[PDB]
Image (tube, rainbow, N blue to C red; front, top):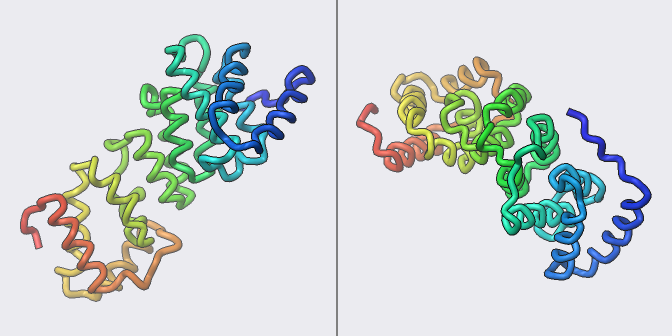
Length: 244
């Protein structure tokens, strides 16, 4: 998994001025120049990753950043000319693209690369990388990757659904829970076991945190009132039987 990102002299001076004329906003002119660049290109996908790496913007990409537009025009280039992945991208090249956009925490750029390189056709190749992130306690990242790769059948509530609830990051965990009905039962069943056990909910929480080694937990939320409000929503939002 090592891309040969080194540029050459025919291409490098061209790129240096491109960064200069990119400062002149982002619109149809900069888009058209990229479309012509990808046309001369041999294997645009591999070069699209090279252009993404050779710009100081790839550390924090946003809609205005040059790195985001480099991949954005690659997506338009693929759809306009009706391009496929055959004989151009390999599982090795997809892994290269995954490592480039998974660390940034930017979901839109990841969703774009999922579409460009067609990650949903071979999503099972990234499961070792997501479980490595779960083992590194990167719940929001691994959780969002699992949602954008549509891995709604690969993970249990303990992998990142419950830790994200511990970290008050209800948004990502509930998004994964909405598309995974199999977990909706045991999740609210587990949250109710904290209350309907007449042991302090803080003791029930601390026992789960120490069993699954949950880190960076937002303790101010783990109390009877805020944890009850979470069970009240998740039982109603998913029509769960009265197993209180």
